[PDB]
Every structure is written in structure tokens, then in C-alpha cells.
Amino acid sequence: PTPVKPNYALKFTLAGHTKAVSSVKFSPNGEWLASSSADKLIKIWGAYDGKFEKTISGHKLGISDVAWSSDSNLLVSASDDKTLKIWDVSSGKCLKTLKGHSNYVFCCNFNPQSNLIVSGSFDESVRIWDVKTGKCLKTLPAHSDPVSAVHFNRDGSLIVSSSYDGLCRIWDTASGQCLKTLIDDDNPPVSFVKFSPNGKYILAATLDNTLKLWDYSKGKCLKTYTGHKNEKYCIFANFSVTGGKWIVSGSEDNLVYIWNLQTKEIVQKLQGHTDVVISTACHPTENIIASAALENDKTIKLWKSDC
Ligand SMILES: O=C(O)c1ccc(Cn2ccnc2)o1
Image (cartoon, rainbow, N blue to C red; front, side, top):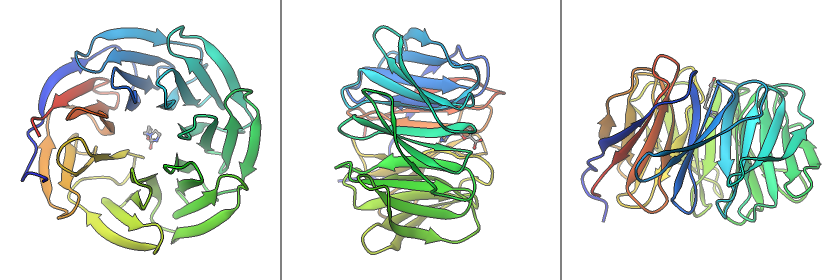
């Protein structure tokens, strides 16, 4: 059962990026953390001991997001250079450069099969790409302002997208056509979305200090999580599932917030960063959180809980 609270404590601080960190993600096999930054670099770190492993270079401008393939062997990154790059993590080599967006690429993810990448851009489109060939399969005219997040569900058949236009939409992967507009407001911006692990729910952030858990099928809000600060940045949120069932997010008051998913109560706030916590990630098997901060800080912190 979910305990009353976790007890995340700081274990490591990872320095090396020279501008704001933009995203952190654990590999599915649990071995690694990948980070991206405005400094144009991807860094790989040991997930359990924080040990710096390597830098992956090649983008010409800053990177906003990085994501792992299901087998932990590839990464995709989204850059202000208007491209995505697919990387072989072991060799550090760029396998493909995905060209087609006409402005910054902000968000990216692989499908579970890891044969497709989805991307979202400041150009207001969502693109779907073939991993093996690097070909753009589809361009969806998804939004009327920059796309803040894109994510596939557990069987790969759906993509959820969000935007500063205020919308959250769900797309059929195979045809590219819209299944549903889940959130149909013109304000506030929807700054982050993702499916829950079982695919039944969508976690959505809006730039009014609010996270919400939605039932995809019914199109209804089930839970709202508040108390943090989020009016400007596209801050990631996570489902923590290895121990207690939490929602995790960074915040513009430099804290990591952790809520009980069911009761909506704040159960812990992690203090230590000295700038906005833009990204958090939850380890796939251990009760470990990674957090990363903007340019007054530029570090990643690894935190561990007993539950
Ligand atoms: O300007 C922002 O909002 C900003 C910079 C970096 C991030 C975090 N992020 C990246 C992709 N999805 C979320 O957000």
C-alpha cells in the first residue's frame, strides 16, 4: 500500500552542463540517466552512483528534450537547430538527423515498439518519423501555437499532444487523424501531457499552477494537484510507481513536489536546487528521482527513498 509519505534524500549532485538543463530521463533498463541542455550537449550518467559516463555532441543549438528507446540502446533529441537526432548510446554516434520542422523542436518520444519517433515543435506541428530510415511519415497540423509535449500510449496506437494554444489532443498513430480534443480551452497554456503507464489516464499541466489527471475514455478530470508554482515553463511531471503511487513535478520555486496520486495531498518537497526545477524523472525499478534545474544551478540531483 502507498505509505503516508516517501523519504527522498539527496544522494548525488551531477555537474557538467554549462547552461540550463532541459530534460533528464532514466533508461528503461535502469542503468543510465540521460540529460540534455541549452549547452547543445547530451550527457550520460550512471543511474545508481551518478558516475559521469560520456558526452554526446552534434546539435548546433540547444537541446530541449531527449528520450530513450525501449531497449535502452538509442536516444532521440530535439533541438533549437530545427532537427532531431537519433543516437547510438554505446558509440555516441548520430545515426540519423530528422529534418523537416521549420522552427525549434521542443519535445520528442519513441513509441513502445521504438520504430517511430513523435516530435512537437514551435512550428505548431507534430511529426511522426520512421526510426530506421529517418523518414518523416506524417506531419500533423496539430496546434495553433508551440507544441509543449508529445507522448505515445502503452500500445503505441495513440499520441497525446499539448500546446500553448490551450489544447490537449489525442491522435490515432496509424492515420494521424484526431480522435478527441480532451482539453478545448484557449487559455491557459497546456505545458505538459503524458499517458499514465496503463494508458487509461492523461496527466496534464497548465500554466496556472495546476496538474490534473484525466480519464482518457470519459474525457473527465479525476484529480487535481496543486500547491507548486508553474506559470511559465514546460515542467515535466511523472507517475512514480516503484513504491508509493505518487505524482512528481518540478516547480518554479526551486523545489521538487511529490503528491499522493489518490488523495492529492503533498507528501514531500525536495529542497536543494537554486533555480527552477524544469525536469524530473523516476527510476524504472528503484525509488530514485532525478531532478534538474535552470541556469543559475545547471546541476542534476539524484534522490533516494526507502519507500
Ligand atoms: O521554456 C520552457 O518551457 C522549457 C525549457 C525546457 C523545458 C522542459 N521541457 C523540455 C521538453 N519538454 C519540457 O521547458
